[PDB]
Image (tube, rainbow, N blue to C red; front, top):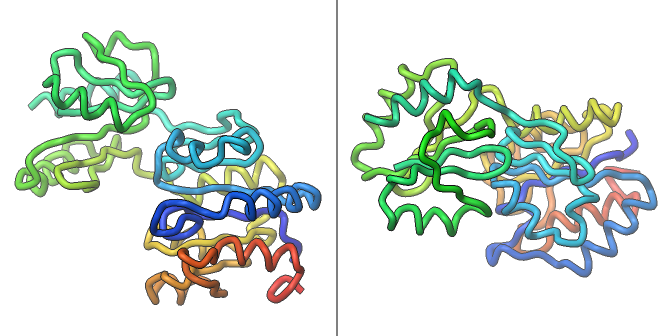
Length: 266
């Protein structure tokens, strides 16, 4: 019944619509959570480097479930990562060679022959982007591909890649003109579970805070599950408890309830 972990999604949850949060209030709150030995976790679809930019003073202290569970960090150190074999990366790239970025542990990668305009645009989206001559030559392992193409081609390319890369990777739509290739069995919720196992804690000790469809599993999992006021009704139905919306510090108010030991933590 004791709160030992607070986990939050970012977009639509810990962040307002302006993609910011009350940093001074959260700092003071975190100082207090640390005194009580309560872990704070950010769990999101977002890139690890996009998550930690929000926490420059806490990034080696709090924990991250990034890239929907393909990357897990605890005390500033990588605890878990997904990866493809040299074999599977070869297979994937073969199929793509019929513009893309490959995501590795140390860098993102693009072909040196890829259109220069595309390479310049990608450079803005990744913390590090390395032009490479050969994908079988790079010393990294890969967990994700991002593909850019005319959006009209997307439904057919998804169908093609779904069968062709079955059991290796799953194609999903991302933004306008983009497809992600993701490792199929890696999810936000099982990324969180990896942290719980490391800490010898149970989902019964967990506060989870979310708003969006991809928060459903994490919310089902946690004993103290909270849907943001802006959450769709289906998410509000899954979560046991409610809080104010993301433009009114709703996630911080949950943390406040834990600190106050008020309901449902009383």
